[PDB]
Structures are given as structure tokens and as C-alpha cells.
Image (spheres, coloured by chain):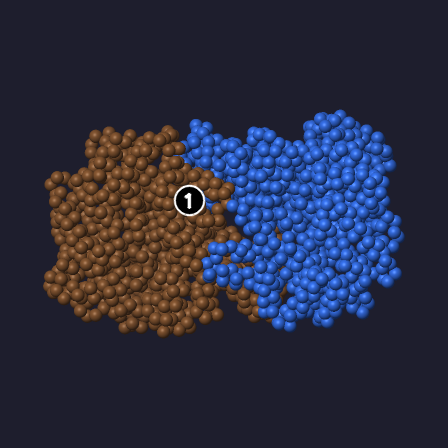
Chain colours: A brown, B blue
Amino acid sequence: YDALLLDRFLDILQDLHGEDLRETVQELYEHSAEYEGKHEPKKLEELGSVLTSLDPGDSIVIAKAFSHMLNLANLAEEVQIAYRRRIKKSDLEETFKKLVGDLNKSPEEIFDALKNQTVDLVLTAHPTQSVRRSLLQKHGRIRDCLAQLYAKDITPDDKQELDEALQREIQAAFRTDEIKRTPPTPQDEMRAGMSYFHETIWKGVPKFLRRVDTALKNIGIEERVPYNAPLIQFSSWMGGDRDGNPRVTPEVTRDVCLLARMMAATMYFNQIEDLMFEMSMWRCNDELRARADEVHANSRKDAAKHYIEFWKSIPTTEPYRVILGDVRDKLYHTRERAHQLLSNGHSDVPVEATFINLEQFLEPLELCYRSLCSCGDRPIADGSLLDFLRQVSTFGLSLVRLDIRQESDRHTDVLDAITTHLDIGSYREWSEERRQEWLLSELSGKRPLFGSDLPKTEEIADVLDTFHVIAELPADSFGAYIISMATAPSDVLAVELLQRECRVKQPLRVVPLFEKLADLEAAPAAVARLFSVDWYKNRINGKQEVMIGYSDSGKDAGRLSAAWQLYKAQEELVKVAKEYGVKLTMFHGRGGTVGRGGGPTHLAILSQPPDTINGSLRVTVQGEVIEQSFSEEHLCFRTLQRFTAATLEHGMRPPISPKPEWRALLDEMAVVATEEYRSVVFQEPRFVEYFRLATPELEYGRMNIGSRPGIESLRAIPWIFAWTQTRFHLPVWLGFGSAIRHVIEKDVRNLHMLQDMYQHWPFFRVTIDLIEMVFAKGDPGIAALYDKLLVSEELWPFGEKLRANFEETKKLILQTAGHKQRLRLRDSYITTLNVCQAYTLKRIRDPSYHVTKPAKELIELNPTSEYAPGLEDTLILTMKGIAAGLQNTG
Amino acid sequence: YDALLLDRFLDILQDLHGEDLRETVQELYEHSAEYEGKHEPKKLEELGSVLTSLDPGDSIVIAKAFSHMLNLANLAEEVQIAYRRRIKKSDLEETFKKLVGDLNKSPEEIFDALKNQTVDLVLTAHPTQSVRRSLLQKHGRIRDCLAQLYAKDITPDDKQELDEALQREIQAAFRTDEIKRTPPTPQDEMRAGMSYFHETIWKGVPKFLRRVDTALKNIGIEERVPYNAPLIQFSSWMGGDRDGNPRVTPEVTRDVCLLARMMAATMYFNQIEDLMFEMSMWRCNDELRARADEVHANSRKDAAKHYIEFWKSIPTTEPYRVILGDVRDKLYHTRERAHQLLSNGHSDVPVEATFINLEQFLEPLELCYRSLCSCGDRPIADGSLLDFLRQVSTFGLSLVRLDIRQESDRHTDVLDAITTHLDIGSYREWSEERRQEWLLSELSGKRPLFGSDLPKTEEIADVLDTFHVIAELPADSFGAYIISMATAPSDVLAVELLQRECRVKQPLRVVPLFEKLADLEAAPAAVARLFSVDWYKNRINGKQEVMIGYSDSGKDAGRLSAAWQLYKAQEELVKVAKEYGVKLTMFHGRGGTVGRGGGPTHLAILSQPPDTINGSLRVTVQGEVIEQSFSEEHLCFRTLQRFTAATLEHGMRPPISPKPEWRALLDEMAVVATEEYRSVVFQEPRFVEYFRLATPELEYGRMNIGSRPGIESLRAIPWIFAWTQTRFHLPVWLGFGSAIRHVIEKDVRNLHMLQDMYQHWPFFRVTIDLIEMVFAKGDPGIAALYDKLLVSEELWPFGEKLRANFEETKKLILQTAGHKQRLRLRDSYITTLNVCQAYTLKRIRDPSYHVTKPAKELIELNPTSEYAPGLEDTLILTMKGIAAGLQNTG
């Protein structure tokens, strides 16, 4: 069945570029097969020899070919998983049954805990989505075709028409330029994020809640999940996160907020007419009777011809139609208003004619529900009306609440300008104590601070104008104000002051972001110091949110040390919040790759310390993970399934708390790990030199994924990207070798204690299992090839030292997990792209192959390329395809 | 499996009204089962005895119960047909294979004939759709649930959720008042008609054409059906037919035209953005390159924020996106313009900014197609772009072309006013010759006729204003001007003159409607006389359309005589058109019931005389048949399948031409049939008396189906309705008895010749088989019950005389067809509703049970009922349910 895609695609490839090129692709496939089988490193050079001969256009076509074959492999894998799972006729029903049987927990406990449980998924425009959207659509169509084929209800002509359809959709994908020729704007990123709503999420949320209802009825709970119960929520960073991204201007934030609002208004408006058609009963309460009579009083006996259906005054015979007709009116005016507000700078549509409240909208629908229940129509109410209720109470008037993020130093620049212009000193030079006292006096005082005439920089005006934009817009359109590089209470209070002073009517919550290891180590002390300020603790209203980054922690220190310190951080932050009687909700800035704290979602949730969630969780979804977890109905369902099940279990089934011997052991082990890590990534003076040569790191910016224009000073995303492309995964496994070897060295019974830890402590089991997965996706022969082709003859043994540690570390990992179904194959295509990337990198870093209308062939697609005509496109294609095969970019 | 619906519904009925009422329904079901089995006529009285006891509300609930059970039976029947047909893994592929094998016809002949073949389906608002739209939606949902259940890929929770869904949707249907409490407006009728487009037809047409492409490729024709080839078209009468309907005002016609136009604009606009997303290639011709560069010149470098997607100026890298982006612009302005034109009386949107031409729209899409084909992307072009092309070239800028119909006497009134005010005589009093000469002189003259100061009546102004409305609106929004009661060329020329004189820029074609038997007999002479006028023959442009009604023909004369005369009519009209070198297309005003020329569509097409279609057919779809043939994907497909296959076969496989002995035989037989028919329906002086008592005819108007406010002088629709409700079907079989008996009486070998005719002449075979079907749906015991309960003791034997002829005629029918799978059952429910209708009719026509806030029970739903509180609703429910069970109203 693996042969199928190969057959169809290679048929199309021959129909588009001839037999010769299809045969050469087949040869590369056979050599790669002999490599992923026999594992002879000579086969790699044997393959590269074939790659050298290729014409400039032909090499582009070859990279294209293995790239699209990898994408098709991803789609076939998704289809086979969905069907192999569906033909069974963690998991929600299994989780409930286990919670009853294992832990003696009762159904009403599960229902109660589930009612008060919340999972806030926030989508980010982090530049990790390699495939352009124009091609993502084509992928969606193709997986639709392959899903309809993998079935036994095919009627011959339907199968033939799906054959023609899949053929033309493959041809369409292959006929599009996969290379973004200009990087996107923030608005484009927000569009790409929000596209999953009016395609999957919007109908996916009600379906998921309905399934939860079914499971609860399978436990004996006739009651239903409350429509207003916030089991899942969505936030966004698209257009809000401006940290290190000057292209996210205030006007961008206005744009994305008006945008999302208009999308919501449109969706509700498309729903409301069909809901009106269904609610055709004539029985209601005295309550709904009175209200419908009220609407029929001010019924506006008019033509009302702007609508298509129900343009006549709705008779009181059908009262639900009266009320929902008013809901339609306020929806029409909401949509037209947001459309004008976005299109122009203003609208003449009266605000009293629109829905301004989150639940001005909800009130009429709530009334319809109470009516249906009172009159015995609870089944009818638990249908389209319940779907609509959940959609309103989940997506609100603006599909997602937007977060704003900014680095603390910009707020410090603003405040410094304010104190200098006020001739009272320099806020920068002030100590922490002084800043706290001053900020407190201004927060409690009633006199305005700065004025119209405050001297501002483009930066200072940028942040001040973002606050004014926040003031101008509706409060339910925003989420949290996240402070990057937060260290002291003064950083938070500076934001509270700048908000109040910029006349922010309803100021949004402030949340510090601790991402570097130094800041996570001292985070509990800082949060406690903030809670110590009574003025802030009284306004925080017993609830506080603090963000915990995962990307940069494992970059400057070891991955093991970073994970362990993260656990410690969560644990002591919970201790602080409990100490101050504040409900702490922690915001996990997790990535897609394990190097940035990624991995299976339920494993990451299980690896959190116990009693740190408590029915309140907040997790980012990094760009590419949006597509990974919401591009199909089944994917979206399995996602919300995984999240809510993991949280509920972590609430009722606490993970084991570590024994003290395991605490001290992991402290020592973390010391050894960090020394081992910084030994090779910072102490070695030639390391940065070897890195910029042996990995394709420098070329990452050429993909134009995001809108954002030494090794300590680079972003974590291309850091994990470089070692993932070369399939070496250094930042994933580095410290573990020396850590384990030192722990068995110091004591031999520590081997028995490691074996003890792997079989009982969830955090350790997950950590080791993840490292084992990453080893299952690695091959040091690739890094050897990159060294032999790109690293100077001098520090060749350096990489071999690394290659040593790799295997050494792997030997230890399986020794702790106690290890020693036949997918493979895709590594053949991946290998071909690896060799192509190495040799292409060699030809790129040369002088001979450098630079000193319409397009009708692939070579004319890059006319402004500093490198040789056909080369740059080939390199970008290699990165794209290798990323697709590994199902991870950075 | 029949027991399933009974189980589920009766469970809901008990959950809504208690065990007692469910048990009484079960009793009625058992008595009806003993009647449809043992056929004891005592069982009917045994059942009515049980019906008498029922409380006023309970009888309403019982009629409701059997009505909804009948509807569910219809839905289960449709699902079982669709699945029983789908599990085979006439018909298009079979028709092609038979055309090749049987008749030696070649593939290119089939393709050529298919290219030049057209089928114009015109939807009518004829008041035959008994079920209100608010309930039709619920039926659609229920059949969705039942279709998803009748399958073996149910995952337990999915099956349970569909259980809950079907339960709540049944409860929702049963909780709606099935009774239209006010009759609709014409605009509502047009909405109900057009709803099938933005739900089924719009996506159904491209799918059907794709299937035709598949079959052609299964015959060896790699070529595809031309996108602009008009294989199927749609016209409408909704808002245009004003014959005897004063509520269809000119403003109504304006309304329905602007309406349909705005619907089309909206649909195209929703399609165009996704099409833009797919066409992401970069290869085009020099042609499309030049045009896309042209658009990019006037690209309007602006924000363009009123759109959601592609608000940035589209780069020339993707030229298809440039062109389709312009198509999006002109679509947006088309939609906004039609929306303002409808909402207000005017729009400021410039006409040059919109699509004004039928193929100004088509030009850019045609260019995109040529581009894709030239660059080797013909598979991509034959996908969404081809679907869109076919949608444009099939639905145009206004989903349907509207017909206008008016009785000739109104045009005569207008012209008479014009000649009297001009003091030149009285057009009414003028002979035909004089009218022809005068109309001709005015048509060829250049001086205006009437002026602003012409004295007009509300009628005269009605028709004149309809012509002005036609002048104000776009020409591609209208179809034909059909003349009711057309007898002479002067009736047509009067319309041509009134059109030209009302400044109708592009005058629409005029078409006479011959529906009464007298007019069909003399139709060929009249059409020939019209073609004799050289002035008209030169402007008709070799093409002429003439309408042929089926409703009234079988009402004043026998059904047999009417059918036979229809055949003769078509045949001699073709002779006339061939004699004048005019391409004649005939417009068949067929109904849903056989009494109005209904029946299976392919049988009706086979029963047309040979060489009378010639790749041009026009058929009405009477109100209820719209739902019957377009409420589901499968239904719509089977419909277009049936029509196009039947026409193609009737083109390449001509039916046998009747032998002359069969001609004379059918002439005699028709004489005997007409005498036998008028003997009982017009000669009998007490017949009208017996009819107004033994049938529920008088009560038809109580259903409020349409917007239209002796027996010779009634409409054919309630005429077939009355004898269909009583399941006697008098107008279907009346004359056949005496006809056949006289033909075997005059000659004994005429029995051998009848046997000869049934096995070789398609018209006769279809006629007899239809009569046999109608007998398969009849039961004289019902008519006996109606007589015994409602007809006075006096003329009881009269009905028995009819009951005699019934059986006698049936004996003859099977004697010609040579006759002597186990569905039945539904006749049990139908029988229950029959008895209920009879006894309820008896209690309605009395004095004791006559008349001398909100609603919280069924009895308060009719507060303005001249009859007893619970009675009228029960009667309407009986008519609705009986109509549903027989799958025919009138």
C-alpha cells in the first residue's frame, strides 16, 4: 500500500517531465533504500555522485519530487491512523472508566471536576510552519481524496472520478511555486491562523462537546455539560506578540482585532437563518411569550427586503422565530458595523443596534433554551440551539482573545522618558525598591502622569500607541499582557501603570514570562515578592497567571537540566500561590519539537508536577502545530480529546511525587548535565565555527516563514532546526550521557535507583521516552556526511567526538528504559534530501557559483538570487522536504 | 425493518402524549392491517367506531400520528431505494451501451447528439405542494439521519448520537403546526422554489456533468462535454405566471427577478474566493500573461480591506489569481448592487463596475481555461474551474429565466381600450382578419400607439405595467411570454405589438398555450396560419416555441381521448414546423399526477411521437414535483439522469410509428371513450351533486398551498385531488371501459390487435401501464365508505354504477397488458386516514358542530374556525396525510 502513492505520483511526474527524470528519481529511491537497509555509508557518496550530474532545472525537479512524496507520505499516514483507529467497533470513555474502576472516583465527581475545568489553547504565529498556505489547501483536498479512497463503499465511477480528482490535485500542488517569494505580514499570519476556524474549529467544538455528553451518559450522568461551561477556549498571539518584531505595529493589532470580530459576526450570521428555520414550535413559557410579544410590538412593519428569507414581519404564532429574528437583526448590524469599521475608519451603524456584550447575544438564546426545556422539548434544545449556544459561549463576539507581549526593557524606556521629562530622576538608574515605591505612588495617586507634550521615540510611541489602541477597542477582544524578560514586580507594576495612564477602561491582566533558566530559577521568589505588595494582591482578585517558556531554557543549559528546572519552577510557583491564596494558572509556552518542550501533548501534561493545573491550563500552539492539530475534523477532535482527557486525569489521578533520593539525585545529575552541555557548546571556542558549517542553520531565514525581520544570541527555533535537519538532535540528548555515567559512577546502586525511577516517576519516564523517540529519528551518518562535505579537514574529529557522545548517550537511554512497527521507508526519501542538501550547501559556499519579465521554467523563478540560478531554490526545497519528512521544523 | 420507524416514532408519541394514545394508535393500525389483508368492509366501520370516541384534541393527535408515520414511510422508502440502487457494485451507461450495441450508433454520434441536446426544466408554483417548507426542512434532516443509519460503518457512539438526533428532529417536526394559517405570497412561492438551488441544484449540476464525462470516457470519448454546452437549463414561473392570479402584480415580478439575481451573485461570490486559492500556478500563455499584466496596471494599489482574504494587491507571480481577483471585484459589486436594488429602489454602484453580460463573466474564466490547457494543466482545468464554468453557463447572472403568462382576453381588453381611445373602432368586435391586418400595420409602422393619457383599468394597467417592468429589467432575466387561451395569430401579434410599444428593448419570445381539447385539435392549423404571416416568420428566426397543456385536456374529455389527441397535436405541429423550416420546441405542461399528464418522466418522454423533440425539450415541474425530484443529492442526480437519458434515446432510438389500423382503431376508441366520459360527468344532471358530497373536493382551498385566491368551470388540480383522496381515480380510467368493450364488440380480431398494440407501440404500452399503476393504488371500498357516510340514500346506486365501471375497466386493462414487491402496509395508515376523513367530513357538514391570546394546546390553534374547535384541523391533517401516503396531491 506504500507502493500506491509512489505509483500514482511517479505516473504524474513522468506525465510532467518525462521518463528520464522519473527513472533517475527511482534510482535515487533504490540507493536510499539500500542505505536505510544495509546502512553502508558508501551508499551516500554513491547517491551524491548521481546527484552531481543533474542539470540546474532537473535538481530543482528532484527536490520537488522527494518533497511532495514526503508530504503524500504524511497524508497517507494520517489517513491510515484515522481508519486504523476508527475500525475499533488514552481516550475519553477509557479515561472515565479508568477513573471509576482504578481510583474509585464517582461519576458526579468526574462531572463536577469536568464542569469547572478549562483548557485555553492559544495559537501563535511562530515561524515554524514551513509549507505555504496556498499548498496547504491542496494538501487538504488530497487527504480528502485519499480518505474517500481508503474505504470499501466505492462505486466504480466514484472511484474513477476520485482518481481523476486526486491526479489533478497532485498536478495542481506540483504546479505551484512552493517558495514564499516575500515574507508575510502579521495580518497574513493572523489569517493563516484564523482559517482553521471557518473550516474546522467552528463546527468541531460543538461536535466535541456532544461527544463529551455521550460519554457522560455512558457513565450514568443524564445531565449535560453546561453550554456556558468553559471546557475549551481559544486565544491568539497573531497580531499581538510584538517582542522583537517591529512589524507588529499598533495598527496591525487594530487590524487583527477588527478582522477576527468581522469573521465571528459573519459566521454567526450564516448560522442564524437556518436556526430560525428549525425553531418552528408554537409552545413557549409565559416568559418567552412576553418577550416575543415585546419584540412584535416594535416589530417594524416594513418590507425588510435586505434579507432573503423571512423578510416579512414574523408572526407571534412561532415565538422562537420572533426572538431569533431579533437576534438576526442585531447580527446583521454587528456584521455591517465591523465590516465598515474594518473597511473604513468608522461606521454610522448605531452601537445600540449591535451586540456589544458577550452575552447580550446569549440572553435571547438562553431564553429559547429555558422555554424549550419547560415545554418538554429538551431534545430539541440539545441540538442546533445547543451547538449555537456553545459556539457563542466559546468563540464570543471575536473568535479569539488576543494577547499582547512586549519585552520589559521597552516599558523601562517609556518610564525613563516619563521621569526624565518630569525632571524627577532616571527610572533606568533607579534601584528596584525605588521603582516599586514610585510605581505604587502613581498607581494609588489620582493625578495624570505624562501629557501630550512628552518627548517620545518611535519605540516609546510604539508601546504607548499600542496601549491607546487597546483602550479604543472592546475589552472582550483582548486577553493578557505578557511581559518578556520579566524579573521584578516593578516590571508588572510598570504595565499596570502604563495601562491605567493610557486610559485603558478595563485593563487586561498582566503576566510575566520566565523563559531563560536564570529567570525560572528565581521565578517563585519574584512572584512571591509581587504578591507581597498588598495593593497588587487586592486588585489581582485572587487569580494570577504567569507564563513559563520552554524554548530558551534548553538552549543555554542542558535539555535535562532545563526540563528538571521547569518542573521545580511550576512546583514552587504553586507553593507561592497557595501561600498567598491566589488561584495560579500557568501559561506553558511549549513548542512542537521536543527541543522547545514539545512532544505528545498528553505526555507533556503528565510530566507536569501534581496539583499545578487544578482545572486551569494554558498552552501555546506553535504555528506548524496549528496545522498538525486542526487541519481535519478527526485531527481537531483528537486534539481537544487529548487535552481535556489529560487535564482531567492529572486532576483526579495525581502523578506520584518524587522520593527525596530522586530529588538529590536529579540535582547532582543536573549539575553534571549542564557542565557537559556548556563544555561542548560554549567552552569549546571553535564550536560556533563548526556549527555554522556542519548545519544548515544560517540558511533558515531564506524560507520567509514569519514576519519577524554568537550562539547564546540566536533564537531557539533555528537552533533546534539546525540539529533536526542534520538528524543529529544534539540539543535533545547532549547532557544525558555525562549525567547518567556520573550517577552510576558515584554509586552502583544508583543504577537500581534509575531503574526504579523510570518505572514509577511520570516526569522521568516521559523525559527518557522522549529522548528515545528522538534517537529513533536520528542517524549519525548524516552528520558524518555534512562534516566530510562541509567541515574543514582540521576539526573533523570534533564532530566525531560529538558522534561518540551521541551513541554513548543512546546506550545509556535504552539502559534506563530497559529496551534493546516497520514504517522505515520514508527515511529513504529523507536520506535523498539529506545528501542533496549537503552537496547543494557545498556548491552554495563557493565563489564560482555566485552572482557578479515573465517566467516559463523553474530556473526563471528566482531572478534576484545572489547564488547560482538553480541553486537557492534547490536548497529551500531541501529544507522544506526534510522538515516535512521529520514532521517538525524547529 | 418496516417495524423500525413504528418503534421509534411510537416511543416518541408515548413520550409526548402517554401510553393511552399510543395504544389507540396501535389499535387503529391493527384494524387497518386486517382491512388491507382480509379486505372485509366491515372492518372500516369497526375502525370508525373507535374513531368516534376520540376527544377533540386526541383526534387531532391521531391524524398527526398517521400523517407523520406516512411521511417517515416516504423517507425510509427513498433511503431504501437509494441504497438498494447503490449496492450494485434506464441509466446513462446502460443507455450508451444499448445505443452502441442495439442500434449500431457510434460514440461520436452519441457525443455529437448529446452536445446539441437541451433540456429546459421550468419550476412552477402550482399549488400542489401540501407540506409546508418549515416541515420540509425537518424531513430533510430526518432523511439525512436515516441515510447515515442505513449503513454498516456506524461507530457505537456515532449511532447513539444519530439516535438522539433523529429523536429530537422527529420531536421538532411533530412540535410544529403543520397547517399554513395564511396562504403564501408569490415571493414566498419563489423562495420555496429557489431554495433547492443553494441547497442541491447548485452543486448538483457540475457533479452530473462530471458523471456524463465519465460515461463518455467509458465509451472511448476522451473529449469532455463543452462547458457552454446547454445540456440542462432552469426556468421559473414563480412570480411570472399571473393567469387567474391577481396577487402576482408587476411589483411581484420585479421582486422575484431582483431576488433571483441577488441569490446568484451571492453564490458566485462565495465560490470565487476558494477558486482563487486553488489557481496558484505560475505558468500561463502569452495571452493570459498580457491580460493579467493589464489588470495589474489598473491594480488599485490600496488597502482593499473590505475583503477578508487577498486584501493585498495580487502579484503577477500568480496570474490566474490576478484575473480571478478581478472577477471577485466585479462579483462583489454585482452582489452589492443587486442587494441595494432589492433593498432600496436604486443603487449608486456603477453598472460598468458590475457584470452586465451573461459572458462578460465567462470571458475571464474561459481565458483561464485556455491557459491551463495550453500549459499542460488540462486536469486542473477540468476541476473546480470546470465546475465553475458550467455553473456560470447554466445558471447565469440570475439563477432562472422567468416566464410571464397571461390569458389572451386581457391583451384583447388592452387593445380594445387602445382602439376605442384612438376612435378607430372596437378591437373586441373586430373579426380575426381585421385584427391581423391592423396589428401588422402597427408592428411595421413607426408611429407610437397609445400615449400617457390612455384610459386604463386596473387590469389594463396591470398588463401594461408588467410590460414596463419587463422593459426596465435585464433581458437575460426573462424567458418566454406564454399566452393562455391562445386561438389565433392575432393573440401572438397582440403580444409582439404590446411589447414593442411598451419600449421592451429586447422583446422576449411569445409562445401560445393550448390546453383545452378544442384548442389542441385546432392547434396545428393556427400555428401554420401564424407561420403564414411572412412578417412574423422573418422575425421568429427559424425557431418557435409552443406550449401544450395536459391538465385541462383530461378534464372535459376522457383521459384516453386527451392523451391520444395530445400525441396527434405534437405530431402535426412538427409537420407544420417542418413545412415552414422552423425549429419547433414544444413546452409540455405536465403535472405530477397521471390525471394531469404526470407519471414516470422517462415513460412520458417515451410516449411522445417520434421526431418531435430533436435535442430540444421543455417540461414544467409542478410545485410538489420540485421537492420530489430535487430535495436530495441522489434525487437531483436521478432526475437529470432520467431526463437527459430519455431525450437522448428518443433522439437516436425513435419509437415505432403507429400502423394505420392502429390510427383508425384509436380514433373510434377515442370517440367511444369521450361519449362514455361525458355520459357520467356531464350528461348525468345529479353528477355535480354527488361529486360535491362523495369527495373532499370543496375543502381543498383550506390547505392554503398557493397564492391564487359547475365542474366544467373548476381547476384540474382539485379535480384530480378529489378522486385521488377517495382513491377511486375516476378521471384516470373512466373512458377505457366502454372504449375497449366497443372495440372487441365491433370486431373480435381487434382483441388480437390490442394485444399487438400493447407489445409494440410505446405510447399505448405507457398509457395502459400507467392506468394499471393507478389501479394498483385504488380501492373502491373507500368510495363505498364515502358514499355510505356522505351521499344521501337516494343516489347511492349511482356510485355503485361507477364502482361497477371501475372494476369492469380494470378487468379490461389487465386483459390488454396480459397480467393477472410486497410493500402494501402503508395502505393501512392511509386507510385509517381515509376513515377519519370520511367521518370527519360527516361531522363537518352538520349544524350542531358549527359556530354561532396565546395557545398552549392544539385546540387553541384555530380560534377563527367556523367549524367546531377541533374539527377543521383534523380535516386538513387528513388531506395532508392521505396526500403524503399516495405521494401525490393533484
Q: Nearer the viewer, residue B651 or B742?
A: B742
> Is A88 located above or below residue B258 in the figure?
below
| In the image: residue B194, left or right of residue A526 | right
Quarter of the figure that contains the N terminus of chain B: bottom right
Task: Rate crowding at label 1 as few (under 14), some (14 to 19) or many (20 or more) other CA atoms within 10 Å.
Answer: many
Residue occupied by mark 1: A142
Above or below — where is B254 with respect to B175? above
The foreground one among A310 and A610 is: A610
Q: Is residue A35 left or right of residue A190?
A: left
- As displayed, is residue B305 above or below residue B703? above
Q: For the point 64% across and 43% down, which residue is it?
A: B257
Q: Residue at x 74, y 34 (%)?
A: B658
What residue is drawn where x is 19% and y is 39%?
A42
Task: Identify the residue at image location x=30%, y=50%.
Answer: A822
Element type where label 1 sits in the image: helix
Q: Could you tell me residue B330's position as x and y percent? A: 52, 39
Q: Position of residue A486 (x, y in %)?
A: 26, 60
Q: Position of residue B219 (x, y in %)?
A: 53, 34
- The reply to whether residue B886 is in sight is yes
Q: Mark 1 belongs to which amino acid?
A: Ile
Q: Chain of mark 1?
A: A
Q: Nearer the viewer, residue B397 or A427?
A: B397
Residue A412 visible at all: no
Front residue of B856 and B683: B683
* Residue A624 placement (x, y as % from top left): 34, 50
How many circles with numbers are drawn on the protein?
Answer: 1
